[PDB]
Image (cartoon, rainbow over all chains, first blue to last red; front, side, top):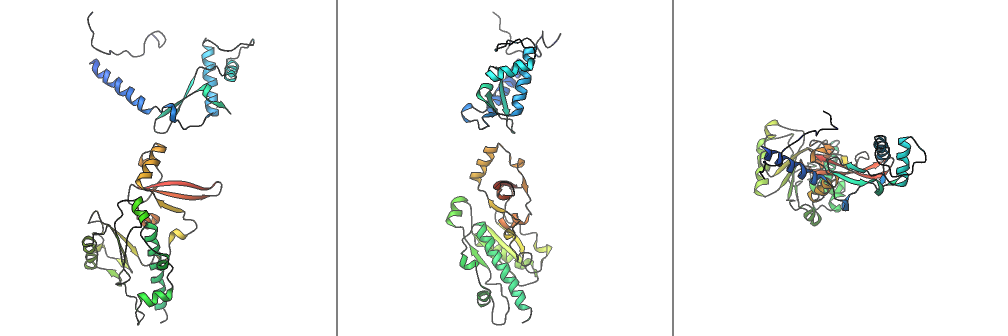
Amino acid sequence: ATTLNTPVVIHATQLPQHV
Amino acid sequence: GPEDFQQHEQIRRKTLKEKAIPKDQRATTPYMTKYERARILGTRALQISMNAPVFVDLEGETDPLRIAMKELAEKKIPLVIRRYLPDGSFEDWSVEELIVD
Amino acid sequence: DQENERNISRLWRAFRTVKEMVKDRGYFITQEEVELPLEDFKAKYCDSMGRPQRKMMSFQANPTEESISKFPDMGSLWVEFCDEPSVGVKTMKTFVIHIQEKNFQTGIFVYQNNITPSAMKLVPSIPPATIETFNEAALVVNITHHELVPKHIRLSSDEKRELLKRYRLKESQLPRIQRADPVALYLGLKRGEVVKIIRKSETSGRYASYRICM
């Protein structure tokens, strides 16, 4: 749980597209 | 939802691209300032101390700052200085593009 | 005549510095009119009885061709004097209405002793025409001739935008010169236009500084 093994912030670019 | 983030990211990238000064018209000193030299040496020394790859022949040396000074002498430091103008606009000079002293 | 001569000398000095002010602001004035001998002043603007009459002391000025090219919006100018110790509202209206009906962009009004508050609320009351106020005293010396006062040159907007884009500045981030600064009054500096100062430095000689009127 550190800035060396997990991303700082995560955001969604678009809506989830089903494949 | 996410599209709010997409708009914010687009705006951030657009403002960043507007602030950047293209290489063809940067009007700052060709020489590396003493402050830039000191910080390049310190940051490169930190990176070497944290087990980064090194681009010079270690003459049996152990001081990371000395290794960084050797890299600067041989112009092998993969760093870039981003000089900031008062308005927030910035230029980008590579280390090998600058002349020390 | 034992002191009226001194009064006429004071009037002559004020007239000379008014002409110098107009020429510096950039309207066509000739060195023949500037370098005007005291005897010529007596023979021209003074009557037989030694009385200084200021009806004909007034004059109209027009921009030079260089000034027209540099600042396209330079209109005509009008300078007026007055013999009364205090300028009245009627005498001030005869100036403002005259400015309007003669289509003058700027007008310079002076007063011998004082200006009443009653006549002070109409000078900014008729835009876009600008009316500026002065005294016959406190003008007898041109402050721009003082060696401490540097050379101030009003900067045109074309080169003002060039300066601002060169230094990546807002208008507000420049050094500021007060709208009521005596040199600003001399130059007729509107707010928002920058002035260029050629400072004689003890170290590096001539270097150009810039202030903004604001």
